[PDB]
Length: 50
Image 1: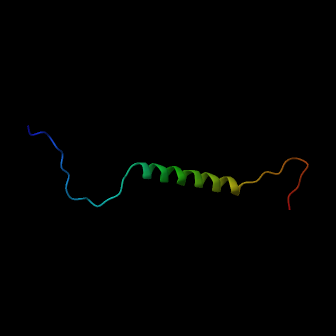
Image 2 (image 1 turned 90 degrees about the vertical axis):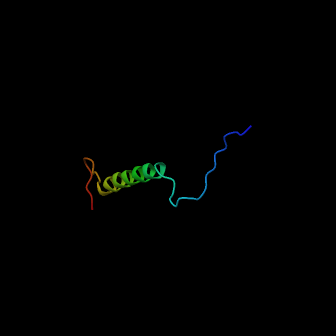
Image 3 (image 1 turned 90 degrees about the horizontal axis):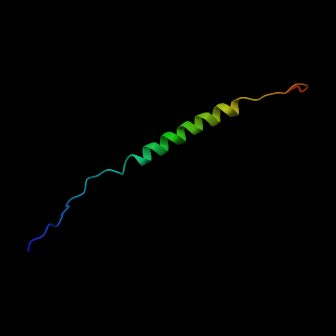
């Protein structure tokens, strides 16, 4: 008896989405945080910086 067979034809151009966006966003946030931290330094008491 005839059965159900799915038939997909043609391809739509594009890339997979969703996971990539999340990862990129996370990376950007981490980079920004890292940059800010690098910009700041602390000199503790009794010390002096040149």
